[PDB]
Image (spheres, rainbow, N blue to C red):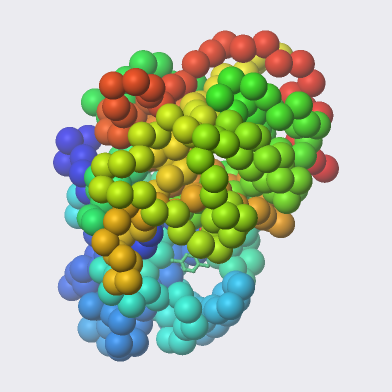
Length: 377
Ligand SMILES: Cc1ccc(C)c(OC[C@@H](O)CN2CCOCC2)c1
């Protein structure tokens, strides 16, 4: 798996992408790695933000499916023409697969101006595939047509330019320290899990854990932030605020309506608490917890032209769709999407940003009763 190490790149805030090839002869493209969706979709027309795009006319192996797809989201969309073609991952396993490709022909607020990626690799399950679950996801096609074991793992580092590794079909023990702790995939649509307890600094929010997962809790490499349902966010923030009263901050800041700025190297992190999520374990009444630092929820905003200081965002926010464990969470950990056994493994990342005081941690076992009742029906 050393072939796959460091095979992800990116810029802060713009997501992590891997190099892929499509069609014959190979067209090289940088493709966003997204565990929060299930479509393999690539730019197929000269949108001006794009370095590159899929030229189907060049590919002997391309086959039109004579069906379109339309993918709306909040303030924007993409849409395209479905087909299949041969796909490889140069710094991945040594296979070639016939995959569904959504050739993106029109879009709105999808592509990022200044980004170096041109497509998206949805790694979640068929259930949430558009237009429907009959459209087989890439990773399904990859496993079905090859002897690649049914799992992948991600080490998202983020140092500006960010970096990481997507190990396809296996686990690289060099990417983590300590032991892997596993949480069940509640259902195969998103990578859905159950949070059973939340501690800020050690103290818990004392809320009906059912809330923590209203209506979902998911692991999503395509989201930057830790999202938290309305009520959980309220209490979450209420407590982080109390942990941090040493200095005063505006209301908008907590709502991600404004950024906060300190002077160069002048923001010791200790006015902010560590945050621990307890996840459902593999065994009845057994959990484990993952602990992240404020260096995870305080993310430097890359470049602001109207300033020169240490201006971080607050990487936590509300949600109507549920908890979303994004890069704020994932960059503390090596994460193993163990699809074969329906579970996600967390371990301390060999690359997470630690200091001389505190660290990201994964610890267990803990005893937690009624973890099932934490899941919404
Ligand atoms: C790069 C990009 C552009 C547009 C959209 C809508 C993107 O979303 C990526 C998804 O993984 C978003 N998550 C949000 C949480 O729920 C699952 C989908 C990415």
